[PDB]
Structures are given as C-alpha cells and as structure tokens.
Length: 24
Length: 24
Length: 25
Image 1 (cartoon, helix red, strand yellow):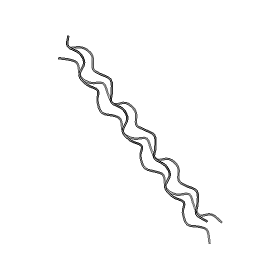
Image 2 (cartoon, rainbow over the protein chains, first blue to last red):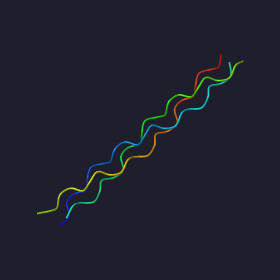
Image 3 (cartoon, rainbow over the protein chains, first blue to last red):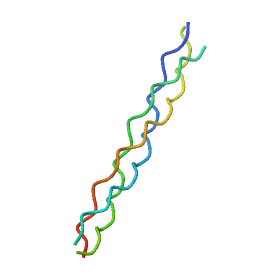
Image 4 (cartoon, chains in turn cyan, purple, red):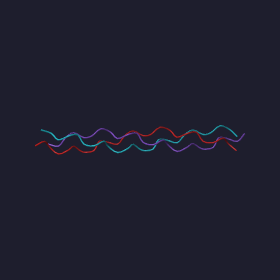
C-alpha cells in the first residue's frame, strides 16, 4: 500500500507591511 | 507507491512595521 | 511493505500585516 503522508511544507512568506502610524 | 504530499506549512511571520505617520 | 513517504507539503500562507508605524514627526 501507499507510504505515509509527507511532512508539512515550509512556512509561508512574511506578511505585507503594516499601515502608517498616526500623524505627528 | 509513495504517500500523499504533506499538509501546507504554517503561516509566515508578520510583515514589517509600517512607516511613520504624517507630520502634525 | 508500504511505500516511501510522500513529499513535503506546499508552502503555508503569507503571514498577517505588520504593526502600524510610529507617530509622525
């Protein structure tokens, strides 16, 4: 019969940049 | 035969901080 | 005997947005 499932894949990439801070 | 692929990897890390806010 | 293991899974999803920037000048 088939072998076991493979391991989990690699982590996804970093997320997008955060929003700008509030005015000065 | 070979097993099925593993599951997707974990989510990536958070994105970088956003830029400074506008001038006051 | 059973087969060899399968291959690694696909990449995970992107992480979430980073934190807000600091206050402006």
